[PDB]
Each structure stands twice: as structure tokens, then as C-alpha cells.
Image: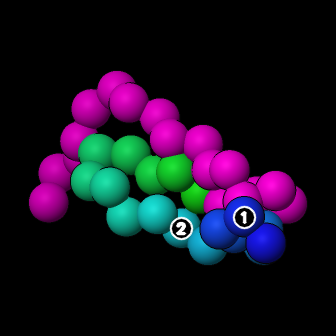
Amino acid sequence: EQECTPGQTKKQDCNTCNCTPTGVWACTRKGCPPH
């Protein structure tokens, strides 16, 4: 119970942290898609 576990999606514009079986997410940083 750190903050997450399943796989919720983190809206951060241009990228996404995504959730994992351990809270800690993965945020990528490259560019933003067309709105």
C-alpha cells in the first residue's frame, strides 16, 4: 500500500507514469502528441 499496484494510468500530458505491481510508476519524457 505505497500508492498504487494494479496499473492505473497517470495523466501527465506528453507521457504517462502507468501503475505497476509495486505502486512506483514509470513516466516517459519525449514529446506530446497532437491534441
Name the one closer to the observer, 5 or 9: 5
- The amino acid beneath tag 2 is Thr
Q: CA distance from mark 2 to mark 1?
A: 16 Å
Residue 33: mark in rendering: none
Q: Residue at x 14, y 60 (%)?
A: 35
Rendered position, 18 above or below 9: above
Name the one closer to the observer, 14 or 24: 24
Name the one closer to the observer, 1 or 32: 1
Report the span colored magenta. Answer: 19-35
> Can you give x and y, in whole percent of width and height, for residue 27 in the image?
50, 41
Residue 31 in magenta stretch: yes
Count of picture labels:
2
Q: Is residue 17 visible?
A: yes
Residue bearing mark 2? 9
- Magenta-colored segment: predominant secondary structure: loop
Mark 2 vs mark 1, foreground winner is 1
Residue 2: mark in rendering: 1
**Horizontal relation, residue 7 to residue 32: left or right:** right
> Can you give x and y, in whole percent of width and height, for residue 10 in the image?
46, 63
Q: Residue at x 27, y 32 (%)?
A: 31
Q: Residues within 10 Å of mark 1 (few under 14, many from 20)?
A: few
**Horizontal relation, residue 7 to residue 11: left or right:** right
The answer to which quarter of the image holds residue 30 is top left
